[PDB]
Image (cartoon, rainbow, N blue to C red; front, side):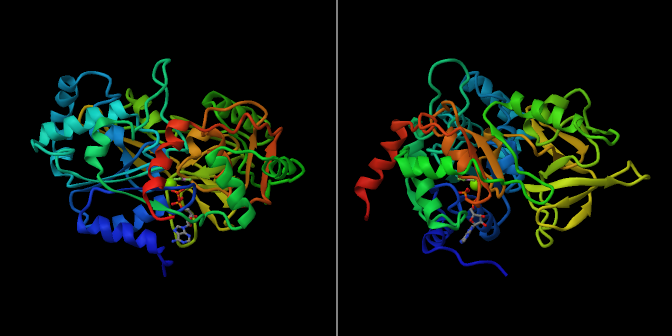
Length: 418
Ligand SMILES: Nc1ncnc2c1ncn2[C@@H]1O[C@H](COP(=O)(O)OP(=O)(O)O)[C@@H](O)[C@H]1O
Ligand code: ALF
Ligand SMILES: [Mg+2]
């Protein structure tokens, strides 16, 4: 009972199916992610792999991080070390077989990584050809969130790679903001992508202080930039609770690798919950009842048997007793690692890093500061609801755009239709 595809959305699929290594791109909430799900529905599913930048925005479209797939850790070391690792039992085949590769949020891949892959691709598989032959279906938003700075100098976007133009000949554009309803909020947020604050932008978003966004016993609360802010916030907000502490330690195929799980995963070693605690759903469960990836709920009890499993009411409204599930990661080695743990993370505080790839309903964000170019746009363009959104301490030097990029979406603009 699925909805209609845009004439554009459709044309991408038509093009991908033929068998073209295409890339696609457009604003926050224009069905980049979703189109991938319907492409993954249409693609012969043997040797067809799916991936993303963030370990979360994969648990979202049911793949793994480009990292864990490729099996070369950080990609720091040279072309000869990197092909050592790809050659290893497990990874070797992972490669040989992939006929089709899909990557969401390409923004947070940094070109020297892309390049170091392309080479390794041609390497193990032995094709004398672009990316070892493999059909690249990519997407992301460049003006959204850019790659994590390794050292000090500026980190280097993916479109700036030398392989990039050689590996993804074609590029096409998505154009309508399906996410957000209200047409003011469409231009309001189309502005901030391009990096403009004239005073109605600034007035309206300032307006939202007096908004009270927090809904049914449940807040999709603050989007901080820094991760230690996030985890710390909650460590208080949960202490600030009368009930007793229910501990949930995991059960990993390897104990001593837990850290690799930790950072590639979406869950903690030790997750701790009391009554009334707020939480989020990190894997999909039942897309019918609507326990999807990114559910906002509140801990309404535990049972007194089993492992005392949590009970949760959600925003979508339906109530389910949560069991533990199982994640696996191709841990640079050719070992697959397991973890058994609840698919819940404490949903008071969430980094802007995590929130990219996702949609939201019920958000807060402080903007009395300056933020890394893009970092502003992202956290705003999460919310569906302009009414159920609250900005704090707004400041127009928050709104920053990298112009290397703006000129990338000018060079494309200036040889096209409108
Ligand atoms: N063809 C469509 N028409 C209307 N809404 C759509 C369509 N495809 C997806 N959506 C909705 O639009 C929103 C944005 O999708 P998403 O894939 O998260 O975009 P992006 O990856 O650009 O952030 C989702 O809430 C989804 O429900
Ligand atoms: F472009 Al997105 F969530 F993938 F806004
Ligand atoms: Mg997405």
